Image (cartoon, rainbow, N blue to C red; front, top):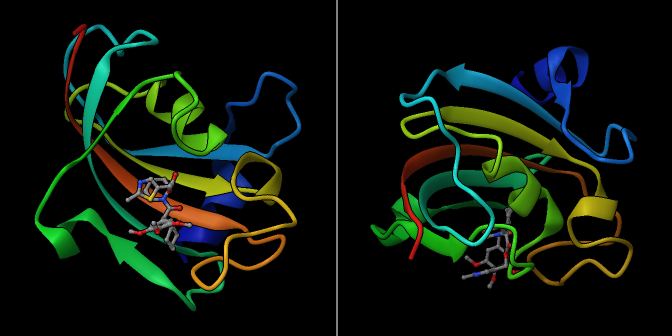
Length: 128
Ligand SMILES: COc1cc([C@@H](C(=O)N2CCCC[C@H]2C(=O)OCc2cnc(C)s2)C2CCCCC2)cc(OC)c1OC
């Protein structure tokens, strides 16, 4: 379903161009601008293992997820991916382990060599 579409049609947003991170824009945002590295970004997300066996949403906690973009505080795929988004945009990310938690994984939530999928909504951003 969503994951497969992304494999087929997603844009490669890696620097190395290794298809480790593919993206589809599902809902177009507003503004002419994305956040700059170091901006504080506010997102909602729904995340799962590509095989659907563990799931997670910021909506489960009724709290936006906040981080400083491109500052290495989260998995690489997020730093790279959210930086491509506009305010109000929803995007689908499909993420090979090298841009997530690699072979070590992070048990018990994430196993070795797991592909991740996220729907992310970029609610807002500010250059703090
Ligand atoms: C390995 O740690 C965790 C990872 C995540 C999710 C995850 O991988 N996240 C959370 C959303 C931000 C991207 C990515 C991550 O960088 O996690 C490190 C965390 C930063 N802040 C957190 C509360 S977890 C994971 C995505 C696929 C379905 C399984 C959950 C949520 C977690 O708890 C909500 C978590 O435990 C702290």
